[PDB]
Image (tube, rainbow over all chains, first blue to last red; front, side, top):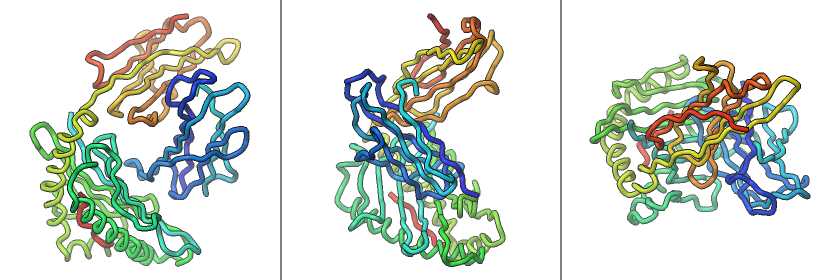
Length: 98
Length: 276
Length: 8
């Protein structure tokens, strides 16, 4: 019955190390609406900003969670997502080719 | 070829918390402009776009009262629909509403819609005649009869042909630089080898508006839509969108494949090819 | 401008 969310973790601009950018985590295609979305650096959650819950024509919702960040060779960024359709929280590491 | 003013409602409950949560958003084409979330301390109808920012005092005072009362009828409606399906009172269920109007060249109303969904499945929907409803279930017939005897279709037909068209025309005029904007995408093809005989070609399309775009891979003219792995269009954050289409090809044959992009921001469709 | 919210 519940629909599994699909996750995309990417940056707004073509990223270069040390240059400030905007990290984004785009979660979509899920149901029920209540979801846990977190952007982490080196395993700890960051202060995020989440858009307002809208849905597509197939009645599945989408959400955008974004923050400011500086791509670095020392720090690795991720995105955690927990849903009722998942047995355990999923994680997607960010890479410039995403 | 047309424009859209669309609203989205969402009401859902959960065990323990009791009082459900209501969220309402409004979009003009692919750009939102209004927000209402009941989780705020004193929930108002808040703007999201710089062209609805001005407006007039009553527009925010009335739509706040409209959205606040809309939050109340849909928390009662959640229990009503649950009772129609006769489900336990301790669970968690959702109600979604999607109404809007598509307008053409000179104010022509091409199509008006107003549909509801319960637990992700279609529940009630207004027909294209805009005078009667269609019901998916038999439990939804309780809502259909209630909306039939109340004459809510005549009310719905008056909004979609009147206020929905004029406000979309008002939005398009006041946000012309944002709504009627047609930004073309910056495109390029990256090349990721994956195995001894396979590489991956990823055809990118970045920073474009509106959202409607076509990304197609072709092998010497033959369409490869079935063999491609298309990704969903994602918002870049600053009002634009991004998209890429992948394809696994034999190693050494990357020059026999071409990516074709189509977007209203480009006067002619593009045809790209990978260069080392 | 929101429309008339009908109660299911």
